Image (cartoon, helix red, strand yellow):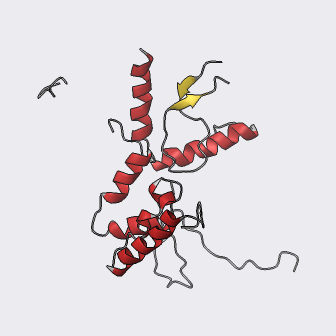
Amino acid sequence: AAAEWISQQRLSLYRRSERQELSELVKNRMKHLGLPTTGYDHQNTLSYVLINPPPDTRLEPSDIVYLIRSDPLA
Amino acid sequence: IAPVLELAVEYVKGYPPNSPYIGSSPTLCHLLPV
Amino acid sequence: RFMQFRAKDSYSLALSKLEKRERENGSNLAFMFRLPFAAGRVFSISMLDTLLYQSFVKDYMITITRLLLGLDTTPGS
């Protein structure tokens, strides 16, 4: 009855995506090198730089404001 | 000839573990047990 | 033609004339009657170029070849 199990994996490997292929390649190399697979567990964002925006622009969350901090020793 | 009908060490069989590259189609192969 | 070359061989030397006639009639398969190729002793990767050019007209051609070669494995094929 092993052929039934073989067919199960065969459909699974055929249905598997490229992300799973890339994910398994990293994990295969990690166990070969001895590193735990967990912790390897995508970038759905768009970022840009605003040079000197007007004083009326709204502050959104996760915003990073470039600062020129004065010399602490002076 | 019968007519065509209108109506119908030993090796393990598995997939090679370490795929060398991405896109290598997994073929069930004759594999060494170890 | 230089795969298994018998210089003192009238038959293989006569195949040269046949391939020149086929090359005369504009045949793209002129190497076809060389004995090593017809026997499967030689092939060229330039056939893969023709496979890619053919796919402009036959979008199934690359898939069919890999199915025959086993390069792609579809369940039930």
A23 vs C22: above or below: above
Asked if residue A40 shows in the view, the reply is no
Asked if residue B23 shows in the view, the reply is yes
Q: Tell me the quadrant of the picture where the N terminus of chain A can be found.
A: top left
Q: Position of residue C27 (x, y in %)?
A: 34, 74
Q: Where is residue C38 in the image (x, y as percent from the top left)?
A: 44, 57
Q: Position of residue A14 (x, y in %)?
A: 41, 40
Q: In the image as oriented, which residue stretches furthest toward the right?
A: A73
Task: Find residue C18 and report its image quarter.
Answer: bottom left
Query: What residue is shown at x 55% (from left), y 64% (from top)?
Result: C9
Q: Where is residue B28 in the image (x, y as percent from the top left)?
A: 49, 33
Q: In the image as oriented, which residue stretches furthest toward the top?
A: A1
Left or right of C51: which side holds B33?
Answer: right
Q: Which of A40 and B17 is in front in this view?
A: B17
C65 vs C54: above or below: above
Task: Find residue B2 and report its image quarter.
Answer: top left
Q: Nearer the viewer, residue C45 or C53?
A: C45
Left or right of A74: which side holds A28?
Answer: left
Q: In the image as oriented, which residue stretches furthest toward the left?
A: B6
Q: Tell me the quadrant of the picture where the C terminus of chain A can be found.
A: bottom right
Query: What residue is shown at x 46% (from left), y 69% (from top)?
Result: C14
Query: What residue is shown at x 65% (from left), y 37% (from top)?
Result: A37
